[PDB]
Amino acid sequence: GDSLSLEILQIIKESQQQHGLRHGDFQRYRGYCSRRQRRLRKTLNFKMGNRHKFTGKKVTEDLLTDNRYLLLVLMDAERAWSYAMQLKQEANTEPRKRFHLLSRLRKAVKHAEELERLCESNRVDAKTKLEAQAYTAYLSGMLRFEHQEWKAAIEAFNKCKTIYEKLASAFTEEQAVLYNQRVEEISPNIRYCAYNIG
Amino acid sequence: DSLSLEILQIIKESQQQHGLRHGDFQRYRGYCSRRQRRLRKTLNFKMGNRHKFTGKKVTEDLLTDNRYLLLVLMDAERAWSYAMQLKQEARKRFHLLSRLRKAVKHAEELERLCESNRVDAKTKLEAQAYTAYLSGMLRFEHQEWKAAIEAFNKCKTIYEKLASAFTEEQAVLYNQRVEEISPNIRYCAYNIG
């Protein structure tokens, strides 16, 4: 039970709401993630160098004695995704921005995949493994949706739904709210995919 | 469920990265202030919206997460850093004692907050141990030897208990804090006689 934990959905939702997404300011949110990531990098560099005064031994043996490296990768994902969503706003009128949109969205999935694999570590708790898999499925669905790959998108969104519903069942109705609203959040996407496979 | 605040791990990693260990006391204060400002904004944002319907049954408050506790911890650390700077910049003794007493009062606030049933057992002990350590330091610098040894002994007992309760890995931090105050305890004892 001294496992690592990362409350991924809680972290991203609370961050997104405070730092710009109340009014679709994805540029503001990306800025925030970037500043957080920089603080995290400096801390990781310090911890990986830190040594005990008496014995001279390293204080922190690897990147997984706390959740900070996991959080650094999550910021990379969130930064790429917010950049993609900014570009989507711009591409509405500037079609030339679509390449850059698609590149950033794929980048977000890639970072989520990296985070998910890190969470497969036996030091990471079971709830976080579910969180990381659900996050990757969400972003995979978003990338597939933007490419109009409707069946692959609905597979990803349905996987996301199934995992969050699993999560919500292991908890009280008060704890489950965030997971349930996340399912509500992707339901318009699931609807749209289903009718394109009609 | 319960709130957790790993007080000793936070203060040691923070003092080490942000200046205090190599005598850049003002840099450490700045870091505490900047962290506080970020915590204040998050807390204001949360509390500012708490009257909105979002599907929850419970209304958020300052003990919904540990951010308010961490805010108070940073006050005690800023006061401690001023005290440490003065200890080095060595009437000025009165200012030293004043800064130490302020750090103690902040720690006492954090300890009272942690009396809440929202806060876990481990965190209550960490808070008690932190207050005891700062109280010991105040009394020690004022040559109140018996009172200093009482506080340091309480501090040592609690950290030994925490060292003895978890992983061999977590024990190292707590054991090192016990090492740190052992010379103070010896000095008190030989003044008492």
Image (cartoon, coloured by chain):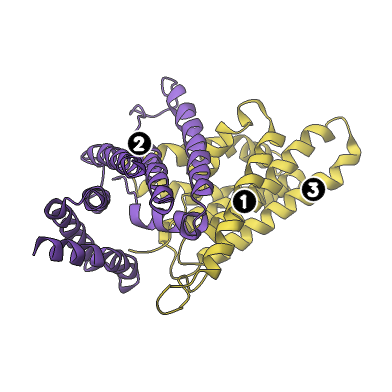
Chain colours: A yellow, B purple
Which residue position is annotated with label 3?
A: A102
Question: Which element type, helix, strand or loop, lies under badge 3?
Answer: helix
Which quadrant of the structure image shows residue A46?
bottom right
Q: CA distance from mark 3 to mark 1?
A: 23 Å
Residue A114: give x, y in percent of width and height. Answer: 62, 62
Looking at the rendered structure, the kind of residue marked 1 is: Gln
The amino acid type found where label 2 is placed reads Thr
Residue wearing tag 2:
B64
The one nearer the camera, A95 or B181, is B181
Q: Position of residue B14 (x, y in %)?
A: 46, 54
Residue at 26% from the left image edge and 44% from the top image edge: B119
The quarter of the picture where residue A142 lies is top right
Residue at the spot 49% in from the left edge and 52% down from the top edge: A163
Is the same chain shared between marks 3 and 2? no
Q: How many marks?
A: 3
> Dot 3: few (<14), some (14–19), or many (≥20) neighbours within 10 Å?
some
Residue that badge 1 annotates:
A37
Q: Secondary structure at mark 1?
A: helix
Q: Are marks 1 and 2 on the same chain?
A: no
Q: Nearer the viewer, mark 3 or mark 1?
A: 1
Q: At x 45% / y 55%, what residue is drawn?
A: B15
Q: Is residue A31 left or right of residue B94?
A: right
Q: Is label 3 or label 2 in front?
A: 2
Q: Chain of mark 2?
A: B
Depth check, front residue: A150 or A129: A129
State the image coordinates of residue A99 (x, y, percent, origin top left). 86, 47
Residue B43 in view (yes/no): yes
Residues packed near mark 2 inside 10 Å, few (<14), some (14 to 19) or many (20 plus): some
